[PDB]
Image (spheres, coloured by chain):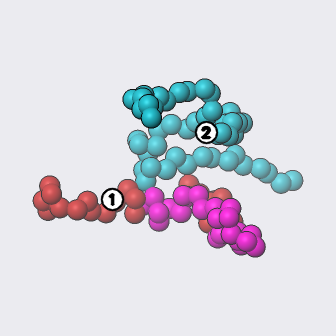
Amino acid sequence: AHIFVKPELVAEIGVKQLQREIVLPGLVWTNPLTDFGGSKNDTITVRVPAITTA
Amino acid sequence: GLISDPVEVDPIQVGRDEAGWVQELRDREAWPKQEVPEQAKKPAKVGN
């Protein structure tokens, strides 16, 4: 009938919440345009050059 | 208006929507796959 007052103690052993690896941002064309505030309607218009027919 | 009033509509937002260059996509979770939205099929503008 011995009772011992002991503390519950919390440990960290490396069990983390499994999460995905991030790969998409490095594969996509990023920021060829930046001056969206500075252009009308927050829109930068990109020009596609002409092609002629003979 | 008032400073405490709810935020009103941005004219830049209205013009941005009326220009029609905001990218609409498909839900990526809808089965069967969605039809391609009309904005996603619009030809390039002849002018600017």
Q: Is residue A34 magenta?
A: no
Query: Label 2: which residue?
Result: A17
User: Between residues A38 and A7, which one lies in front from this camera angle?
Assistant: A7
- The colour assigned to chain A within the rendered structure: cyan
Q: Nearer the viewer, residue B48 or A39?
A: A39
Residue B43 is drawn in which quadrant?
A: bottom right
**Residue drawn where x is 68% and y is 69% of the image:** B30
Task: Give the residue displayed 55% in from the left and 27% down from the top.
Answer: A12
Instruction: Pinpoint the chain carrying mark 2.
Output: A
Please report, as a chain letter, where disc 1 is located: B
Which mark, residue B10? 1
Please name the residue shown 55% across and 48% down the image. Answer: A45
Q: Quadrant of residue B31?
A: bottom right
Chain B representation colour: red
Going by the picture, which residue comes out furthest to the front?
A1
User: Which residue is at 47% across, 65% downward?
Assistant: B18
Give the percent coordinates (x, y) of residue A1.
45, 35
For numbered disc 2, what is the local secondary structure?
loop
